[PDB]
Image (spheres, coloured by chain):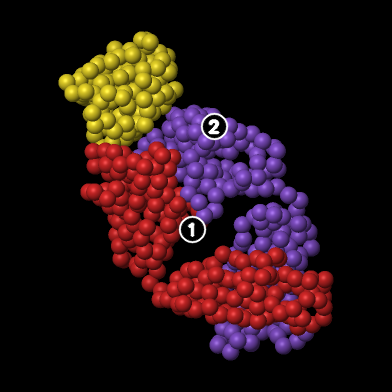
Amino acid sequence: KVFGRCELAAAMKRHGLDNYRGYSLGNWVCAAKFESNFNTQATNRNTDGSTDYGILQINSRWWCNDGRTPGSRNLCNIPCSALLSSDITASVNCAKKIVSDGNGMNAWVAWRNRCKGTDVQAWIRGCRL
Amino acid sequence: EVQLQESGPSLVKPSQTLSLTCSVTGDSITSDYWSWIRKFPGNKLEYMGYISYSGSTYYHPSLKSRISITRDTSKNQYYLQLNSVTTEDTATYYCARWEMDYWGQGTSVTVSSAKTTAPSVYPLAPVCGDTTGSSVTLGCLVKGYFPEPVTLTWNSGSLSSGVHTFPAVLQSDLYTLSSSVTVTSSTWPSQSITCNVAHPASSTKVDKKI
Amino acid sequence: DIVLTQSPATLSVTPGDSVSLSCRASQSISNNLHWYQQKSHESPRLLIKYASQSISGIPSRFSGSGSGTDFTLSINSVETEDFGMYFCQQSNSWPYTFGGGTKLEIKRADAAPTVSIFPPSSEQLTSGGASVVCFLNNFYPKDINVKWKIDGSERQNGVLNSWTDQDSKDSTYSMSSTLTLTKDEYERHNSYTCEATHKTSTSPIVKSFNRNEC
């Protein structure tokens, strides 16, 4: 499904990303926007054999298992298929593990290039949450 | 499924550095996030810190930068090293996966500068006087030993019912514990009752007939 | 840091009935609150993660709810093996912190302690030491007031207490209270008294003996 801006905002908040390890809700909304345009089925095959799945494009070389990637590790111990559901639970749970690393959100390239440093608060602007 | 287990000295001296090893099976060490949690005598739990995929670590400020968490290059074991310890670091240490789903059994470590000391074992007979009751309770006092633990039995384990053995408390830098046994009055001393106490550290085991 | 408060620290329950455990955070943490069950001589077992997400292999009777600063662990129809320690922990901000814990114990009828006092043994005395031991066994609830008196005067220093865990069978607690003195001092007094006041009676239980007399 394709979430609406405020809808995802309310969703991510209920799923507890707002101010998770210091990252404001806007950061997560902004990242989802540039990473997948709020599409839970967003999929991208990378030069190697990995693929990014979900609203946050989690990679199949490190975080999830898609059965066709060389050197996979499945750190989130989840099928890559579960990161495509309309229920963002698994996607949020994995994202929390990812950001809990030293380089935090920098793990999301789209976020670095388009959200990092910017006033991401505008992304939840206008939402009554 | 993964399995974890802590190992390292059970006794560490003040100012010395405490080291523990966590062996993991069922999942690659470099393929995940790993933690160390400790539980103090008063049962309170403290999250010590964790190391993640980039090799980055997060330590609890309560540790005042005395903690180091490293992963082994090839044995599938990560470590915990804590500098300048005091008796405040006496606790049960657990290594667990960041997911908080799989934990090791946990291992105890005491920080003390005390020296191995066999316990004095005293027989506790009831105060002198009449048969003031239907049942009678006797006791055994284990005092002045180190380090823990001691194993106490009554009549070499033949008497287990009506027994109460209390947790050891630290007294004058050495441990002390006691145990009571309650039996039908008419059975003692007719049917002898002996306290047996063994202390690994000093390789001693004594018997004290009540 | 984020402080997690769990109240009450102890909760009595009768098998078959249900209970709710509270965990409050000094700062909103959204859904980043997890619940653990911990038995003696055992590592914590994860019961619920992220406030209400269930864990595989955890009896369905356990459930978690709440968000922000107020959380609740619910145990529907408590069973015998549900007794022990319950902790909550947050992962919203570093450092992760734990709540002080809530003890889940078995409710039973109140019972007065069986008090016994023992004088310093001959062997110990022979070595210059003198400990007067007092056992208060098989009582309920756990709250108990034990006082030591030497010749009427109350003595606080040199007393050390130890309690056992709630018995698996009769669900009672037992207590040990020892008054340690040097032989020098022990022999400069006549009567030693162990006095216990417990919920079961407004009249204290008094155990005493006089040096060298029966």
Compared with C13, A117 (above or below) is above
Compared with B174, A1 (above or below) is above
Q: Colour of chain C?
A: purple
Can you say which quadrant of the picture contains the N terminus of chain A? Answer: top left
Say which of B95 and C212 sits in front: B95
* Chain letter for the yellow colouring in the rendering: A
Would residue A102 be visible to someone looking at this image? yes
Would residue C153 be visible to someone looking at this image? no
Say which of B28 and C164 sits in front: B28
Q: Residues within 10 Å of mark 1 (few under 14, many from 20)?
A: few
Q: Which residue is mark 2?
A: C64
- Chain letter of disc 2? C
- Chain letter of disc 1? B
Location of residue A123 by image quarter? top left
Disc number placed over residue B41 in the picture, else none: 1
Disc number placed over residue B68 in the picture, else none: none
User: Whole-percent x and y of residue B106?
Assistant: 44, 53
Label 1–label 2 contact, CB within 8 A: no
User: Whole-percent x and y of residue A60?
Assistant: 28, 25
Residue shown at 24% from the left, 42% from the top: B55
At label 2, the amino acid type is Gly
Lateral position of residue B58 relative to residue A49, left or right: right
Residue shown at 76% from the left, 57% from the top: C111
Lateral position of residue C62 relative to residue B48, left or right: right
Say which of C3 and C105 sits in front: C105
User: Whole-percent x and y of residue B119?
Assistant: 52, 78
Lateral position of residue B100 relative to residue B57, left or right: right
Residue shown at 70% from the left, 65% from the top: B161
* Chain letter for the red colouring in the rendering: B
